[PDB]
Amino acid sequence: QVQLVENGGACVKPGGSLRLSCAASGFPVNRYSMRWYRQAPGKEREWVAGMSSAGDRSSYEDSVKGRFTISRDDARNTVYLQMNSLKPEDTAVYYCNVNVGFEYWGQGTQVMVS
Amino acid sequence: QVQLVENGGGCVKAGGSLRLSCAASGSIFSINRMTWYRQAPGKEREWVAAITSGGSTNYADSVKGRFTISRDNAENTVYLQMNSLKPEDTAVYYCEAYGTYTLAPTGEGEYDDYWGQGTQVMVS
Amino acid sequence: EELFTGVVPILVELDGDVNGHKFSVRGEGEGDATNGKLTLKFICTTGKLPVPWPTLVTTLTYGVQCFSRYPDHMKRHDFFKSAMPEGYVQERTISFKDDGTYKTRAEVKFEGDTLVNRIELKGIDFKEDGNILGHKLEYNFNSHNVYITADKQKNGIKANFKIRHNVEDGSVQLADHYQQNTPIGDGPVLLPDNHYLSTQSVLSKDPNEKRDHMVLLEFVTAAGI
């Protein structure tokens, strides 16, 4: 029915940059908002970025404020998240969440600065 | 209770080698067997390595020839060396102590299963 | 557990006082404990609900955790079912992320042949234009986990968890939820060990009812043992 696939997770040195991507199938992206959650190994899941259904407004948290650039593409049916300069605090993995119905969790991709 | 701690989450490119250590805390009389499992974001759980108190070592068909396992009962800790790490096995890793017989001096003990938090390992 | 075999009607009553705003919510529906299914509708008796529905979803539904599908080996661990015949009291303290606190007291008991939940809520230390008071929360509830542990000193079960509430701007608010239970009946509590209940919530509106619908379909499954 509804599924998510993430990509772009690669090992990056501090000060580098990578472009996380989340594609979805089973719904239109514009009609529903999408969020990104950060989970360190063994730690509680947290929220880093969120893009509303309209896409004209986006929200971040203090830790990653001013670094991420969340974007959406209806033609590609995919959302993207930038990282600007990486820091060790971003060692946690990233999950893609979209609550079209019930609750859906993306497979996710790993991102460790190392 | 017994807490398992994982360490060794380094970044190694194709052909690199990194060591993952799983250390068991608390008072444990013995461990039946320690195993390493690989979990990908989109794939089911698959066992990587298994080592028993008797010294028997079990590896997967693909894992054989690349990973080595060594557990010390007195040090009650297991080290997995990922020689010639491949891009495909970029998944997270977990450690399992199937048998955890913890015996207290008073004579009261427990035998259950405990899970250690995963170690983030990936290849570029 | 023999009481819950089959389908059981569920009735819920809530009377909340959020910073002087008094709202009464009446809810009716059914639940199949065997399949761990809960189909309810919580219509706000008042004209409008001064707070977002997702904030009170936890107060209304998670008070009724006796319909959770407990595995066979975990059947003995269901404290709610064990103490349900005489009912129980459930006190929740809910600390929002810098947006005040809910305090709620609920009584769960069988009346006639129907389950009844009498709930009294009170929210304090709220900031206007916030995530809750500002109604920025979208109408949807995500799946969550509730950790459950016994307490012999109080002879009751204690729960802890964090609830993630979505927001229109994309922010996610983390609310801490702490639950204390007291068995009304004097019979054996049969309190369990540590275990986590996973809840899946899908929300909907009915077309017919002009008033607030608050149609809720929940599936709760216990695990961890």
Image (cartoon, coloured by chain):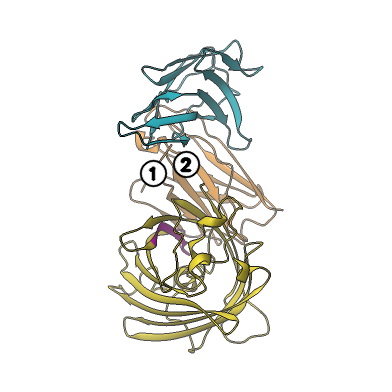
Chain colours: A orange, B cyan, C yellow
Residue C203, picture quadrant: bottom right
Q: Answer left or right for C174 relative to B89.
A: left
Expressed as whole percent of the image width and height from the top left, the position of residue A70 reads 49, 48
Looking at the rendered structure, the secondary structure element under dot 2 is: loop
Instruction: Provide residue C95's location: percent of width, then percent of height.
Output: 33, 64
Vertical relation: A11 (above or below) C97: above
Task: Report the front residue among B15 and A86.
Answer: B15
Q: Residues within 10 Å of mark 1 (few under 14, many from 20)?
A: some
Local SS, label 1: loop
Q: Chain of mark 1?
A: A
Q: Residue at x 47, y 51 (%)?
A: C195
Predominant secondary structure in magenta? strand
Residue drawn at 60 percent across, 33 percent down: B45
Q: Nearer the viewer, residue C4 or B92?
A: C4
Residue C38 visible in the shown view:
no
Q: Is residue C164 magenta?
A: yes
Q: Residues at badges 1 and 2 in contact (C-beta under 8 Å)?
A: yes
- Front residue (pair A64, B46): B46
Please state which amino acid type lies under the numbered disc 1: Arg
Residue C174 percent across, percent down from the top left: 39, 58
Q: Is residue C115 in view?
A: yes
- Which residue is painted at 68% across and 69% down in the image? C6
Q: CA distance from mark 1 to mark 2?
A: 8 Å
Segment tinted magenta in the rendering = C157-171
Instruction: Give me the disc on residue A67.
Output: 1
- Count neighbours of disc 2 (C-alpha within 10 A) and say few if under 14, some if 14 to 19, many if 20 or more: some
Numbered tag placed on residue A82 in the rendering: 2
